[PDB]
Amino acid sequence: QVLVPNLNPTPENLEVVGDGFKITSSINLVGEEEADENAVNALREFLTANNIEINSENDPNSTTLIIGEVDDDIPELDEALNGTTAENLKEEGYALVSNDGKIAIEGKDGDGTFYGVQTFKQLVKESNIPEVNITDYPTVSARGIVEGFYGTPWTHQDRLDQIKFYGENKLNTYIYAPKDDPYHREKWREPYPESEMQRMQELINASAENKVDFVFGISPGIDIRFDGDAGEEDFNHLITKAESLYDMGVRSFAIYWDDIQDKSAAKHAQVLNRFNEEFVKAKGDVKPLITCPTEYDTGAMVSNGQPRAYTRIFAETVDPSIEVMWTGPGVVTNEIPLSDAQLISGIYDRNMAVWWNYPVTDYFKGKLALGPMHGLDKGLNQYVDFFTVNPMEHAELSKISIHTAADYSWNMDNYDYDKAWNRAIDMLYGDLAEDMKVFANHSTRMDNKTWAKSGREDAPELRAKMDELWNKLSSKEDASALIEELYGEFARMEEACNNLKANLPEVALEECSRQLDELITLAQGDKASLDMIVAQLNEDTEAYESAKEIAQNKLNTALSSFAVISEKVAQSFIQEALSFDLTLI
Amino acid sequence: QVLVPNLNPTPENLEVVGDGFKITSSINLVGEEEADENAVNALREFLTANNIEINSENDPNSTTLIIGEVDDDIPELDEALNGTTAENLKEEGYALVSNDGKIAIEGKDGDGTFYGVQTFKQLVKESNIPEVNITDYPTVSARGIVEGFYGTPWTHQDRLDQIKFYGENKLNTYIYAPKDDPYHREKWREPYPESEMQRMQELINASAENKVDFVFGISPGIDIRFDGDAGEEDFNHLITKAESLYDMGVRSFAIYWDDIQDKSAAKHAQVLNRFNEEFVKAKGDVKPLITCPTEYDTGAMVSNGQPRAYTRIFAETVDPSIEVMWTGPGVVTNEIPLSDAQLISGIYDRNMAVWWNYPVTDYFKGKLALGPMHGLDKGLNQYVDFFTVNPMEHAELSKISIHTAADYSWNMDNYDYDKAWNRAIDMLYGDLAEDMKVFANHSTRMDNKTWAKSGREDAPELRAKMDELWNKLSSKEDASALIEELYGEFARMEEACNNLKANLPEVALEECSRQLDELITLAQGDKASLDMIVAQLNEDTEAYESAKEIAQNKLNTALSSFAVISEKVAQSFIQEALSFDLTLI
Ligand SMILES: O=C(CCS)N[C@H]1c2nc(CCc3ccccc3)cn2[C@H](CO)[C@@H](O)[C@@H]1O
Ligand SMILES: O=C(CCS)N[C@H]1c2nc(CCc3ccccc3)cn2[C@H](CO)[C@@H](O)[C@@H]1O
């Protein structure tokens, strides 16, 4: 009475200074005319949605809401704040104060005020708001998503929903770069058909409405020509393509050189340099150029602590103001330790950009990647200024992990993966969060068994209970309490998935139904594996064989089926149980 | 210009002193009346079998062979030896010199002469013998096999052949202790039927002829009673059972306490101490008593560098004379480092006996264990004086592993596991050795997925090549030459197994035919995996789908089979290749 709701991202400084209060049926609004337009529209939108009416003329005992920027002439704003302010904060910073009848939102800039509104929306539950002092700002200057995967691109409606979602969670960057949009890569020289041009316009419009930088990516590297008139003809295709998007309102651009056979470092860098001179600077209001080199992970860039030839030449040729992305120690890796960022930053003598390949699943499509940002150093901001994730072709389920990315990039120093994971599912799933937690917990780790691995381990608590079972059984100690307990877990998995099948909204259900079925199967095979152990302990041959065929048939279903989940946990347990000989005397 | 053939075990000191010579069709035998009877019978058997006649009257043109102990009075021996003796060597040591038509075998004791004859037998190839100076003796004084596994016990013929094989490889210990002989454990109180006693007499006799200590094990722990009249009766049952075996010539005995629920250390030890006194000492010619405690691996014996309650009590109570067995840091474990032996040896303050659970496969019967002794500290002899291995229910194929155990325990310091394994297969398989190497190289590592793991990794060099293929393909580099090399390895795996199916003697083929077909299946799936990769590289979609279906069926077949082989190499490669998504374009 009254408690601070789940917030995402976690604000830098939040203090509870009171007991909280109810916001009236209709309110007074001060500052609308000079405040940021986007911020105001997000406020209006929320206020309409929560049945809250705006007064035509001040009343004295309605709740008052004041909104604006530090540069603005609003005396009531300086008053309602009472001490704390956004003057001392970096771009996108804001102060928010809630004190008996008065909510004050002040941004350092228009972005700031918009962000303050988002926090305000998350603060209000039931018309009740807690009494708080807040100053808030991002750790990392550029935070967001690169739609950069292989497979079916996000639908136009998907992206519009993603862009809204980025705004709500203070993500400011969306990179358009679908490997399978023909006009982005395969037919990069060719202009967009009129109908896609108009859909693009809506995206840029929606991006501006949400303080998101729409970055238009192009990948010419498969066949771009570099020398002579063909080099001239090709460079002019790049400029043409860029201009047609610039004319629609695009102010951020990327040229990418990943996943190509050509390794002409000097020529790649020189294309970038010419585009930087003839397009970026010449336009004057365009953000820094973004790129990634053909060598983009530490394994590929560095040999024996020294940069390899391509990287060396690229690093020394590419202009200082161009943003360079890299993926970490590997393309899909467990971790980015600080020493890796330090290494790559020093090779490039600039703050680096990260293209994090998680939750992307294009390389192992059967598994859903449903875990938090995991493995990333909490001091990465020392060498990184731009942090993006590559998501799954499954736009709705990608939100869980994107939600944690939003918390990690905004408030890096206090990021707790486990807490951000739980908060993400809570905020996204409502009355279904506990069940969605059970399911998603078994689907966080990605491993193609060769070059690609990343994510928190699947269901670690349950894994540790399984190990303890084998430990007890092999030590020939009583294990019946732990066995009773594992029945509980396997029955819980199955119930959770069934409830999820019955109650998930279609938008989520269409992306995960097969994996839900997989987990039910594995749970059933897990339970039967228990029956099988109990039978051996009881020396009941009949009951053993009968549980064994069930367990083996469940395992066979799970292995033959497209969906993949819980490989090292629920699936491995069946394998472990079938390989454990308790028939020894 | 000989050369020295393969020898097992590796002699302590061997030196080539010349070019070698051919032994004549007929020879002069000196010392046959005075030297060890068992050594002479072994010698006569070898001569008979290699068409070498013995002169009844001396002939200066014939090769001269001289045999005896240091304690024997023989002038020719001393003369033929010329500087080298067994005088200052330990028990079981011998000297051997072959030089200028002379071969001199001198043992330190009768056991060493026998082993001298054994080295002679390995030295002669087609009447040719290298000219050598040898002094030789074991690192460890008790070396052998404990038949102590669960499963079908070895047949009577099995055991007779093993005992001969132990003789030839200088193994001096055989512990009879099969878990599923009802009279060993299940009905340990009940006497052996007379026909089984006759079978025992032949075992005892064969052991004596081969300098092997036949050790009679009994395991009363499931239900022995300790207190009052009940315990007295059960103690006399142990005496009776041992007496009946002593009466046939058994002079070593073991009483085991493993794999039972009753953890009464003081009682177990009291039983042992009583048996040590009223039986072993009462008899004067019985070797030290052998046991294992209910806590017999370091995880079960120790907590924070200190003994657990059972172990502490057992160690304080059990007589210093008694040999105590332990299995290392776990029951089935990768290694015994020196620090483990030192720890256990300190607790019991005595040199320890080792029960090594490799090549035993009772806990994972589908896999054959065909690797060398691996993981055992080369300095173990400082705290261990007794080394035995627990073999597979498969007697014949156990020989590969046992062969390397003979070399490790006899010549510990110079033991090379790769060399010994290679030598074992060369010596045992003859013309089939190169093919058997290909197959057995895939079947060395034991792993039940949970508590039990031990042995050399399966096909290491092939594993590293597969690793390098994935490292090239995921870096989009040219991998043609390496692909080609892999096609060759896989074809070779198939060729070897097919040649083994057609030409292996039945006694070995009976034990591995399922594992032969399984490796052929995986080899074919491996090939198909390569096909699938090359199709993906060439964008040939239909050849890919065709290869995919084959790779997948071959894996499914192997996974379904009782037979297990090459989990982490040949089998894993298919899973790796199916998960490697190269259709992303
Ligand atoms: O990671 C990058 C650029 C990093 S700044 N590019 C893409 C990329 N390249 C790789 C490794 C090389 C490879 C590509 C396709 C098939 C096999 C290996 C992985 N990935 C990502 C995950 O599959 C894929 O989504 C990306 O589009
Ligand atoms: O190891 C010993 C005494 C070592 S001085 N005893 C035997 C033994 N006990 C265990 C662990 C307890 C266990 C037994 C059956 C099923 C599951 C666990 C393993 N093993 C060996 C490997 O299977 C088995 O061959 C042995 O007969």
Image: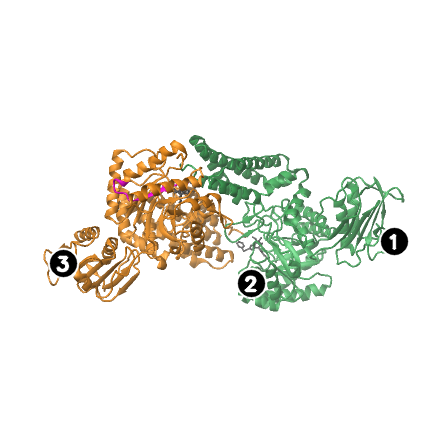
Chain colours: A orange, B green
Q: Position of residue B182 (x, y in %)?
A: 59, 53
> Tag 1, which chain?
B
Q: Position of residue B156 (x, y in %)?
A: 66, 47
Is A327 situated left or right of A396 in this image? right
Q: Is residue A565 magenta?
A: no
Q: Nearer the viewer, mark 3 or mark 1?
A: 3
Q: Position of residue A504 (x, y in %)?
A: 28, 47
| Vertical comparison of B495 with B239: above or below | above
Q: CA distance from mark 3 to mark 1?
A: 125 Å
Q: Nearer the viewer, mark 3 or mark 2?
A: 3
The magenta region covers A246-258
> Tag 2, which chain?
B
Residue of label 2: B301
Q: Earlier in the sequence, mark 1 or mark 2?
A: 1
B175 and A217: which one is in front? A217
- Marks 3/2 same chain: no
The reply to whether the residue tagged 3 has its Cβ within 8 angstroms of ligand 1 is no
Residue count near mark 2 (Cα–Cα under 10 Å), binned few <14, some 14–19, many ≥20 = many
Amino acid marked by disc 2: Met
> Tag 3, which chain?
A
Mark 3 element type: strand
